[PDB]
Image 1 (cartoon, helix red, strand yellow):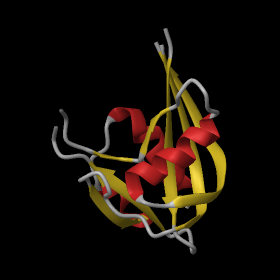
Image 2 (cartoon, rainbow, N blue to C red):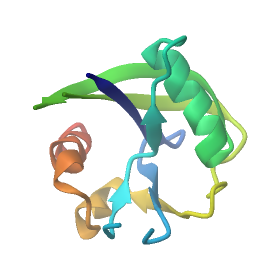
Image 3 (cartoon, helix red, strand yellow):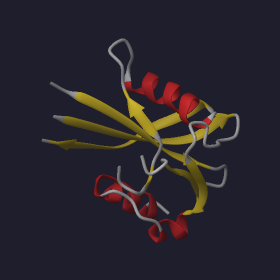
Length: 124
């Protein structure tokens, strides 16, 4: 049985910074691209837009698939979020950082996100 995860690289207007979040150490301890599970009556894109509402307070208006990752069954779709309304905040009690792309390397991410962290960095 499958589960499907969407997650977001939330970009500022210059695309020099991304918004990144850390959950109350529920059970690990790491920063992550905000997201959640896609529900049975919605598309990926739909789920991500909704999730960034719940998670972070923004209304997504522009996004684009960035990278997909599969694991043995577990489906991960990362998108680019380039325009939104609202300004993002930790709406669910999490830590939120606006972090210079330069500096992204500086933070601890679960291994799942590492290739995405590096792709963001490579795509300056």
